[PDB]
Length: 90
Image (tube, rainbow, N blue to C red; front, side):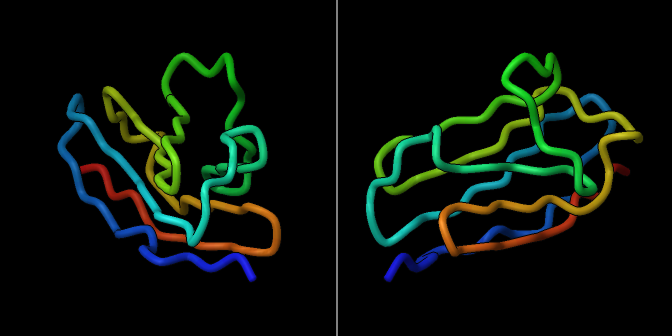
């Protein structure tokens, strides 16, 4: 079974700063199989604010410059695994 070894963590960042959400899976799953969401909206590959990466077991969602409207619930979903945490923008 696919497991999440390391779950997302809540993050609080100042406006303009970088935020990142990461998780680690039990096996290497290509980035194409993962879906990230902010407040229920799927993150798109041409979103100028958010970057999605994967390296082996390690998946990440990066926000280079946080703004207040980015705040809310981050979801990661891959196969049957789901995780969530919260972005707070100070």
